[PDB]
Image (spheres, grey):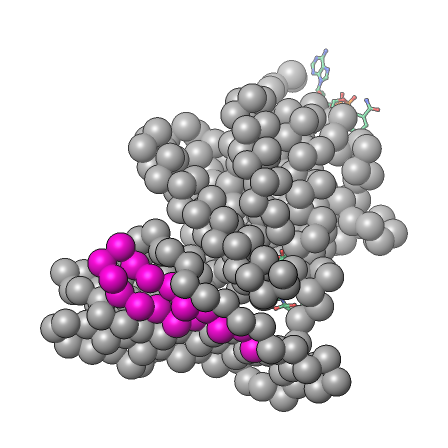
Amino acid sequence: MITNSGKFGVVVVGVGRAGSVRLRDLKDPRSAAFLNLIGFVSRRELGSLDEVRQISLEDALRSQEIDVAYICSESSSHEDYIRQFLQAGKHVLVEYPMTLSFAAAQELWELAAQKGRVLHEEHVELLMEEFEFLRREVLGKELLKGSLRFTASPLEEERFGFPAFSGISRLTWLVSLFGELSLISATLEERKEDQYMKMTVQLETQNKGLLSWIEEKGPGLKRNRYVNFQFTSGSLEEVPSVGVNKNIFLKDQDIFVQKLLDQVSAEDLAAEKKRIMHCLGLASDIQKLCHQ
Ligand SMILES: NC(=O)c1ccc[n+]([C@@H]2O[C@H](COP(=O)([O-])OP(=O)(O)OC[C@H]3O[C@@H](n4cnc5c(N)ncnc54)[C@H](O)[C@@H]3O)[C@@H](O)[C@H]2O)c1
Ligand SMILES: NC(=O)c1ccc[n+]([C@@H]2O[C@H](COP(=O)([O-])OP(=O)(O)OC[C@H]3O[C@@H](n4cnc5c(N)ncnc54)[C@H](O)[C@@H]3O)[C@@H](O)[C@H]2O)c1
């Protein structure tokens, strides 16, 4: 018999850590009712991964069975892939940062609207158990001053982008919790000899709260997050982690599916886009302050 599936055909682009996780999740029962994994695109000659076939980029853009593209490649290639798939009429889910350029991001949102497609930038950091804790903590409190520092191993800027972009998840935490921020200063310390880098950013909330955001990367440095928020009524210097954020990417996919089903209000869609663009704008400005 001839039956037209009501499910959205998905192609995963880039099979690194994120891509592998997306492929795994697309096989989960939580993905069964609305999504159909068609294949994956890779710059390497894999041919297939288990029962999932590799499809050339050219064929993926042409295929009428593909309705959605998950862009999981390195940051520097996101812009190009997003543009090609939107132009081809496919909905797009892309891992943050969607681009390494504010202007480029503006262009892509406009293109998505033009083609009537959903463009979704994944931000699992807002779905973390640790963030739920912070959301409850800041509720009804006035931020006087605070600091958020994240340390980790070296990361190739050429592939993942400038630190403000590669670590935009930390900035997203701050903007989500305290609203739009104004940039006061930004400094970048680079010791390529020791594969070391430290970016220090000073931001200000609309309530005069002063925030310090530091991103540090160096050999041997363990992945650590330091939080210190001082409020007018109470303080916070530690965020517990008792879970492992299981199925966090499926939670993000669930949001994307709600958009595909057109079950997200215009207001919610607008608020999210405004936040995304504000963060990308700040990252872009921070880069200029550090490089110029
Ligand atoms: N055409 C190509 O070269 C090519 C290459 C790759 C993928 N595809 C994909 O294949 C799908 C369709 O083309 P296809 O030929 O490959 O698939 P297909 O025709 O081999 O699919 C077969 C299924 O359709 C049913 N069916 C088809 N015509 C029927 C009829 N008249 N009466 C009763 N049942 C019928 C069969 O019984 C069977 O369940 C699309 O999803 C397309 O993207 C096509
Ligand atoms: N891997 C994740 O958990 C995750 C979460 C959100 C966004 N992303 C984005 O996915 C794309 C590539 O991701 P990948 O992990 O699949 O490729 P990858 O497999 O090439 O990554 C190799 C290494 O880089 C690290 N890494 C990747 N993106 C990073 C980032 N923004 N900041 C700090 N370390 C990072 C990984 O954890 C891993 O140790 C990038 O655009 C990235 O920002 C990845």
Side of 18 relative to 57 (left or right): left
Q: In front here: 292 or 207?
A: 292
Q: Give the range drawn in magenta.
A: 198-213
Does residue 88 appear anywhere in the picture? yes
> What is the residue that sits farthest to the right in this orientation?
45
Q: Is residue 253 magenta?
A: no
Classify 86 as above or below 162: above
Residue shown at 55%/85% (left/top)?
A: 222
Residue shown at 67%/71% (left/top)?
A: 155
Q: In front here: 70 or 228?
A: 228
Q: In the image, ligand 1 is in what quadrant?
A: top right
Residue shown at 17%/64% (left/top)?
A: 142
Q: In front here: 95 or 106?
A: 106
Classify 267 as above or below 239: above
Q: Where is residue 248 in the image (x, y as percent from the top left)?
A: 45, 59
Position of the N terminus, as image quadrant, is top right
Residue shown at 41%/68% (left/top)?
A: 202
Q: Where is residue 161 in the image (x, y as percent from the top left)?
A: 65, 60
Side of 280 relative to 107 (left or right): left
Q: In front here: 46 or 277?
A: 277
Prevailing secondary structure class for the magenta stretch in the rendered image? strand
Q: Where is residue 188 in the image (x, y as percent from the top left)?
A: 58, 73
Q: Is residue 210 magenta?
A: yes
Does residue 67 appear anywhere in the picture? no
Q: In which quarter of the image is residue 153?
A: bottom right
